[PDB]
Image (cartoon, coloured by chain):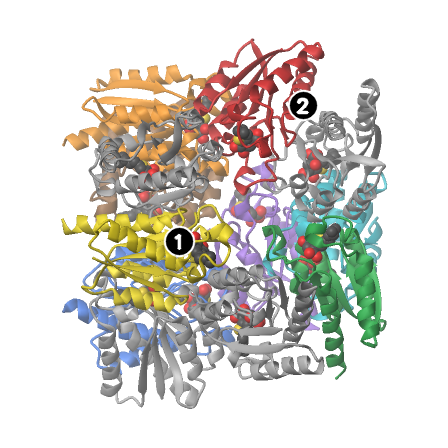
Chain colours: B red, D green, E cyan, G purple, H yellow, J blue, K brown, L orange
Amino acid sequence: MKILVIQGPNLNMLGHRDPRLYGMVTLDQIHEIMQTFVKQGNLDVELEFFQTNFEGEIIDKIQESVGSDYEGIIINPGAFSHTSIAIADAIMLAGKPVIEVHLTNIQAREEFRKNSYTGAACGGVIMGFGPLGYNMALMAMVNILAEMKA
Amino acid sequence: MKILVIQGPNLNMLGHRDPRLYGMVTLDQIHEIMQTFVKQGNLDVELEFFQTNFEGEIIDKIQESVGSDYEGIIINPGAFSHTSIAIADAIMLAGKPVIEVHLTNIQAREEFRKNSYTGAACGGVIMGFGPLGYNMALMAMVNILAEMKA
Amino acid sequence: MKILVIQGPNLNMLGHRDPRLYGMVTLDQIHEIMQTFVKQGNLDVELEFFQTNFEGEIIDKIQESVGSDYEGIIINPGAFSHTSIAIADAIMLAGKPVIEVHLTNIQAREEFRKNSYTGAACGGVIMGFGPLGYNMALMAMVNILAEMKA
Amino acid sequence: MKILVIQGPNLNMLGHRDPRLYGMVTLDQIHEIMQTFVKQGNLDVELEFFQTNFEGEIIDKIQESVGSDYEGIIINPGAFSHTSIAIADAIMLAGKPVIEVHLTNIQAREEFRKNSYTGAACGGVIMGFGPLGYNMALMAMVNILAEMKA
Amino acid sequence: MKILVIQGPNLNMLGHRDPRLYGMVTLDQIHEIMQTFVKQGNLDVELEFFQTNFEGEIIDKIQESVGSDYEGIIINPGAFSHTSIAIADAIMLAGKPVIEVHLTNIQAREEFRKNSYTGAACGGVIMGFGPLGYNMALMAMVNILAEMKA
Amino acid sequence: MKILVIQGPNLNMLGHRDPRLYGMVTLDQIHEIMQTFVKQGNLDVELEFFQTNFEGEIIDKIQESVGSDYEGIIINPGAFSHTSIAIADAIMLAGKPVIEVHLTNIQAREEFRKNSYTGAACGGVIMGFGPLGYNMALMAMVNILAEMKA
Amino acid sequence: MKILVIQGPNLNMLGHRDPRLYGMVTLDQIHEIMQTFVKQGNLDVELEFFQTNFEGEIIDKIQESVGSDYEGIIINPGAFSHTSIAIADAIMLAGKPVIEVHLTNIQAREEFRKNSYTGAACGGVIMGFGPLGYNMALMAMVNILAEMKA
Amino acid sequence: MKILVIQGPNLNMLGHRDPRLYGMVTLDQIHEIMQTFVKQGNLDVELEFFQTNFEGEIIDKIQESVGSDYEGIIINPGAFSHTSIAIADAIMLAGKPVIEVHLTNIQAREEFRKNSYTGAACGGVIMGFGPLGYNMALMAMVNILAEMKA
Amino acid sequence: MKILVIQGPNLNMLGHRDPRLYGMVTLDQIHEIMQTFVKQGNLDVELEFFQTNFEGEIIDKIQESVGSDYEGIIINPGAFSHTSIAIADAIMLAGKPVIEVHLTNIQAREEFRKNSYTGAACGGVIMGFGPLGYNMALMAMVNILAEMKA
Amino acid sequence: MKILVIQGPNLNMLGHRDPRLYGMVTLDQIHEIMQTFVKQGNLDVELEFFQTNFEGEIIDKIQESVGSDYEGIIINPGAFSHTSIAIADAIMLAGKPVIEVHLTNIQAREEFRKNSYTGAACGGVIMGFGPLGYNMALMAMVNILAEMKA
Amino acid sequence: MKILVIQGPNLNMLGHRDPRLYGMVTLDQIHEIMQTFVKQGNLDVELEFFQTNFEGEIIDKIQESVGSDYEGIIINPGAFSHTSIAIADAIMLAGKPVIEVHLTNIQAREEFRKNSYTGAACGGVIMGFGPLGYNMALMAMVNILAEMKA
Amino acid sequence: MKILVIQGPNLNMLGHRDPRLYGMVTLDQIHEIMQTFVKQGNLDVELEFFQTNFEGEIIDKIQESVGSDYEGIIINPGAFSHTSIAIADAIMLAGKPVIEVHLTNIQAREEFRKNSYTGAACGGVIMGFGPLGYNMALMAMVNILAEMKA
Ligand SMILES: O=C(O)[C@@]1(O)C[C@@H](O)[C@H](O)c2sc(CCC3CC3)cc21
Ligand SMILES: O=C(O)[C@@]1(O)C[C@@H](O)[C@H](O)c2sc(CCC3CC3)cc21
Ligand SMILES: O=C(O)[C@@]1(O)C[C@@H](O)[C@H](O)c2sc(CCC3CC3)cc21
Ligand SMILES: O=C(O)[C@@]1(O)C[C@@H](O)[C@H](O)c2sc(CCC3CC3)cc21
Ligand SMILES: O=C(O)[C@@]1(O)C[C@@H](O)[C@H](O)c2sc(CCC3CC3)cc21
Ligand SMILES: O=C(O)[C@@]1(O)C[C@@H](O)[C@H](O)c2sc(CCC3CC3)cc21
Ligand SMILES: O=C(O)[C@@]1(O)C[C@@H](O)[C@H](O)c2sc(CCC3CC3)cc21
Ligand SMILES: O=C(O)[C@@]1(O)C[C@@H](O)[C@H](O)c2sc(CCC3CC3)cc21
Ligand SMILES: O=C(O)[C@@]1(O)C[C@@H](O)[C@H](O)c2sc(CCC3CC3)cc21
Ligand SMILES: O=C(O)[C@@]1(O)C[C@@H](O)[C@H](O)c2sc(CCC3CC3)cc21
Ligand SMILES: O=C(O)[C@@]1(O)C[C@@H](O)[C@H](O)c2sc(CCC3CC3)cc21
Ligand SMILES: O=C(O)[C@@]1(O)C[C@@H](O)[C@H](O)c2sc(CCC3CC3)cc21
């Protein structure tokens, strides 16, 4: 399985800004942890990582995934979760499993973070576990894709 | 007349995804149908087609149209219809006729599709006719631009 | 094809009142223009025109259309667009194509004009083209009814 | 007892349109069933049936009932339930028992059907039993009018 | 001056129903009082009175007034005040002074009576004076029409 | 047929408190009246009555009904109608006919009583007939269960 | 009869500012016109005029009116109409007739002017007649106070 | 570690009702799967399982957990997620990690399921993975409790 | 006088959890303080204390109070204040004085705590005084019950 | 301790107007009762009483209290409770205990009385006990100020 | 140029209360800083400073400014920004430039501070710069008044 | 100090489109005016100017500023002010002073312009001064950065 990991606006600043709220582990470190989760698990998974601050680049990437290459997406759309009907539509149209991850619990913050157009379009959502959420999503994606093969 | 046809996020997937809702005619096929409508009508129209998943590329394109080249725009902003005040402002500022087209009837879907900032900025709106909407928009634009010349 | 053209409350005052907003072309003139569109197109269309200020007369007329006589409706429900669930239900129940036309762009006026119960019930909606909208609707209806025959 | 049965907009299409939602029993058939309920019950009831798509005709009829002739009303105002403050006022002013019936459960459909101005004005409301609701209303009206005589 | 007095749904029941709220003076009595106000004032006014429970009949009547006959309207639209965008549009389009009267203070009742589409379209509104409101409206109309002549 | 009659919070106080609004007939008296309706009708119905002030006891009881014993439920959830998504879900999951009864017209009281999650989940709803509503519900349930057998 | 005329915030600028919207007749001129209406009518009325930009001074004045001196109030609370629950309470507590006047039609302006706490507390409201509204209010007050004496 | 697994209203019907939406795996089967996840992982975890349809029993259980016995809770509050401020407070007061699981994606259903008072009180939330969500929660809890020990 | 003191969900954790917000005085300590207030005052009061996390147990207890034993209730419904229409109805139906106490100022916290269905049903409400509120309520209840005896 | 008792708009009319709702005890009588509560209690309290219908006079008075003279405020802001952010800010800025009292239960009246900006700024709120509320507030203030000294 | 500086409710407490949020610079100090800005700039400006906690005194002052004396106003209406339609109207009617200043960023605080009726009436608004905002406003006013002279 | 000036969507059209609302001074002219303000002031400021119609390019630029090069940002996000939570987050995360400027008063336009996510994230906001706002922002930034150095 190729699994695409899409990281949205501002995620590249992880570990460098607002450590109180988002922690001290960087985005690159999360990606190395995900690799280690696959390698140590001997999972038949190839991870591709992609970060961007552009809505259009997320949509382009999701559309790129219409192919025999990629079998699922794990996405943290950042602030676009709450605003991007376009990304939500791209997810709906992807026709492959998509899992949404948030570092924080978006039910427990400002009112404007409670809506997730993208999350509503995803099969499942994981929030509030920090970096561990991405490993949870990896566990879940492997299990989903194996279920679909069976 | 040069008429610019702008197609927004996800429109490039037409005919390939969710055929139940959006049909089996591709974006390229719609564009060939529009050309055929002009050629068979002997209309003095040059069509330029542009698709993008980027809000900023739509705005750049609309601004590009401030010129003796282009006389009107037919636009399907996709999901940005409901979210993009920036595109709505660009339309307001274009100072040339703009017609909004939607494949679907955005009054008859989710509540979040009912608002169209962009449509409110356009002279007219056409929705719910599938690909035929673009030919309706072409008919209308030709008639508007001929009225303005008179 | 028999196509029924239903014009709602206040439409009979067109061309005589508020010309700034609704123009100087009368309702009778629009109807003659629609005929000319059919005759010059050699379209196999018989138009029937009906105007009324009564919700109940619109519903009676729509129900009248349950028959081998009429194959589609083009309707401008006027202000009843925003208020009449009853007309919306009649449209839903008609089981024939219905197209809604507005002279003005009802996305670009008072907040109370944005809701269209009737438009949500229609296959398609055309707004903001003035009288030309009715010819667009005629073009569209002919194409829809020909598609259904095929 | 004279009991007036008022059937609102679109009810005359019952059994002929949207059978999935509203069933295959016609309005005339419901009225014959109500008669049979009275005759087989030996109830001292004279039914008068009235259907109309006009709000004003419902109000005129309700006002007609200010008389020694009619002792109660069973009404299905159709879509006017949700919109007609005027009919609600007529009901309030009738000074005789009025029972509202809906074929469908208007709590379980679109948000715009949940409000019933007319139902709020009625003594009681019955919804979601299809045609049987009218017999329930008949049972209830007989019992109410007998209680009032005692 | 011909002044048209339009009385909306349920007004014909005045004095006969809910006397606690609407009083014991009938509609016919109000009309005789208005005549007496004109006659005793030696006002150069011809009153025409019209009551109806039909929205469409109000609109037809208002349109009838597009003429050298009638110079102003005093209207109590009843419950249609709160619902009828169509009547509000007819008033806007009338191009003659229109005054709205309510017997009751519609600011001091149910929340659903607070909106008056028709009142917003009228030059002025009078509410809460019972039958006296109509004489106030007559005083006002005479003064307005005399100001316009000067 | 076994028919389960579930009476929710505060119903056990009927006839003892607030007689102006809820009447002077006790809950036990309503239950005896329902029995008499069955016995005098020679209906093949076994009634089981259950009252509780506990949401969880209502849900437990509804789940108890997943069995060859009980064929339908008549429920007055009291105030839980407006609040209990859990009871609404239990009703949805019951897979047997459920009818909601209210003594009062919950469209005609405080705004907070207008929502009925439970009523939306029920096949039908009866409100505003006082104790008679339960007999109406019994009539209806017998007719529904006989229709299902046929 | 002593009639107190209370003029609220900004009314003292009438005729001097925004003549397009509020006209060119000053507050002092309106007061002289009201006197002339009484004198020419030989009405047994003593007018007292009071203008202030202070909510507390309006309330003090209204309370001052608890006395054999003053029999009614005509009030234009200006912008306090929309905000002042305190003035609304003072009006409720006055136990004498109070009539609210607005120069403009507060149904036809900004959304924030539509609410009138004070108007809801008044017996009647007059709006949209400019200065003439005050004479209408005077006519009405005389008639109300004469009715109360009878 | 003792981990308490709390299952709320209606969860005991899993696998027996509405399999389309909630699947065919029973609650007991999920619990055996969780045990197998611990046993096969050689995790130092003792699971305690508790299901109830009572809000008060959930709160009692959570309070029971104030002790050296239990170190974390995995909870699916069912419909109480959307309604129970009391359970949310109990979670806040527990002073131990709590993870919320939903079988379904509560962002993608009825509007009334979008609010989760309980989820906002939890450290993290997992939704839309069916039974697998509970294993994800187990993975997460073990990792959280191990982090806290370090 | 027997005075029933009802303490709702989570109150039994007082003094043990979240001392910053709710203080360090336990529920048992508050109850001993209330006794001391009665004993030192030589008040003719018998206190009965009852805490529960169950809505149904509160309602059962309130209904228990329909008797010559208990003359008033002091209640802190906890989180049920904001949610429980059922408890509010039980209070309305109790026909004895009920006083609501909150430790905290529920006007000064989350928006979801501002509504108190139960408080609206109570004669009076005391909030924000911590444990002292219960003594204030005791002072008040004694004075109310003595006034009723006179 | 000097305790300032501030009474807001309309409170000076207590006992003279609307006795049904606000009772027959005057403001002066409440103040004498408060004195008697202090004198009979031998409390070391000096009361200062201040009533005004002016928002600005309340704010001036509260600011006056920034001094060694006054140690706490008991305030009934009347209708300004619901409207005055300015008074709420003055309370926040006072840096001394402030208790809000309402005669009536402002949770149980019009929707517009439910918001209390001032109450949210106060340490505690007492409502619905009539004049007794002020003695409750006095009891509470003495206890608060004694706690602060310790 | 005479420039009037109006400071609203509570501003006189600046530097003495809540220094964390509003700083330690007093109102008098801000006024001396503004003078120094004019003197050091050799600006042809005469400053007049006015602080008050009374809405009516602000309106009186603004009206005072209708004169050859004063050419512009810099205003911080304090909490009246969010509530005072009357002050907003006075500003609209002033017919001279008015600039609104807030010490804090009123977009970044409580929801109830986001609305500024007064700010909407002003030419420009400055917020969130503390005392420096007043010097920014002075810079701006000088530039505006010089532009108007040219 | 390096100060970054970020200009958002559509700002590049300034002076060329809608001069009535946005004036005739171009963006390049504003930038030259800002330079002149620095040069004539002998301010130790290096301005960098950046305009874009892309949300992602604004975020990239803001992140670019995490460096010893740039010390503050002046931003006009255009229409993204009202929509872009992503840009608001980037501003929050920048950890350097950011000032928002709008040419127009966004409190005085369409309702949809009133929300500014970005402005809420900024230290301060300036609106309604046209091009002068940018010089005000420059004055302010210099003063802020000098205060931080001290
Ligand atoms: O919790 C999450 O994962 C969010 O998706 C919630 C979003 O509401 C928010 O915009 C953001 S911003 C962000 C990266 C912040 C990093 C430290 C620089 C993550 C998220
Ligand atoms: O009906 C339309 O034309 C819409 O503009 C309505 C928008 O709400 C929606 O986001 C989308 S997505 C889309 C392309 C979908 C294509 C099959 C891959 C079109 C539209
Ligand atoms: O733009 C349209 O076609 C509308 O359907 C929009 C509706 O909101 C409105 O009530 C009206 S009124 C009207 C006839 C006005 C004619 C000059 C006398 C048309 C319409
Ligand atoms: O369920 C009901 O009885 C309703 O009153 C609910 C209303 O919301 C609705 O407009 C309609 S339309 C209708 C007649 C439909 C018939 C098959 C042609 C009934 C009703
Ligand atoms: O106060 C008024 O004049 C109203 O226009 C207010 C409307 O809200 C209401 O529907 C009605 S109904 C009515 C006639 C009632 C008559 C005794 C049978 C008048 C009015
Ligand atoms: O009208 C009904 O049947 C209601 O279900 C409506 C609900 O809103 C309400 O909580 C209550 S309370 C109740 C029992 C009251 C009994 C005299 C002690 C019934 C109901
Ligand atoms: O139309 C009315 O009478 C109003 O009461 C409506 C209010 O909304 C408004 O604040 C104002 S301001 C005002 C005096 C304006 C005068 C020319 C300086 C009157 C009114
Ligand atoms: O998806 C979930 O896990 C939910 O927590 C979502 C809730 O909104 C809902 O009430 C319910 S009902 C339920 C058990 C249903 C079982 C088949 C009988 C689970 C849930
Ligand atoms: O302030 C109050 O008294 C409240 O009634 C306000 C409610 O909103 C809240 O749910 C709770 S929770 C609670 C007990 C908390 C105890 C330390 C474990 C009290 C209350
Ligand atoms: O109940 C209370 O104490 C209130 O603060 C509630 C407020 O909403 C109301 O404006 C008023 S008016 C008032 C004095 C009324 C007196 C008999 C002349 C008190 C109050
Ligand atoms: O930030 C501002 O300038 C405000 O105008 C915002 C308003 O919302 C607020 O009421 C207040 S209160 C105030 C003076 C507070 C001083 C330390 C005693 C200023 C303001
Ligand atoms: O007033 C401002 O500075 C705004 O930021 C307000 C925004 O709501 C709006 O989208 C726009 S569009 C714009 C550039 C318009 C230029 C003439 C082509 C500026 C702004």
- Kindly tell me whether residue J29 is visible in this rendering: yes
Percent of width and height locating residue G132: 66, 49
- Image check: B45 left or right of L18? right
To which residue does mark 2 refer?
B136
Q: Which chain letter matches label 2?
A: B
Q: Secondary structure at mark 1?
A: loop
Q: Callout 2: helix, strand or loop?
A: helix
The quadrant where ligand 1 appears is top left
Q: Does residue E18 sit above or below K51 in this rendering?
A: below
J148 with respect to L24 (left or right): left
Amino acid at pointer 1: Ser
Quarter of the rendering occupied by the N terminus of chain B: top right
Distance from mark 1 CB to nearest ligand 8 atom below 8 Å: no
Q: Is residue G36 left or right of residue B70?
A: right
Of the pair D79 and L132, the residue shown nearer to us? D79
Residue under disc 2 on the same chain as residue under disc 1? no
Query: Where residue B61 appears, x then y in whole percent?
Result: 49, 17
Q: Position of residue K40 (x, y in %)?
A: 22, 27
Question: Which quadrant of the view contains residue D142?
Answer: bottom right
- Relative to D46, does residue B126 appear above or below in the rendering? above
Q: Amino acid at mark 2?
A: Met
Residue E31 seen from this side: no
Q: CA distance from mark 2 to mark 1?
A: 46 Å
Residue G13 image offset from top left, x and y in percent: 52, 43
Camera-side residue: D15 or E81? D15
Nearer the observer, B74 or E147: B74
Q: Is mark 2 within 8 Å of ligand 2?
A: no
Residue for badge 1 = H116
The quarter of the picture where the C terminus of chain B appears is top right
At label 1, counting other C-alpha atoms closer than 10 Å, the crowd grade (few under 14, some 14-19, many 20 or more) is: many
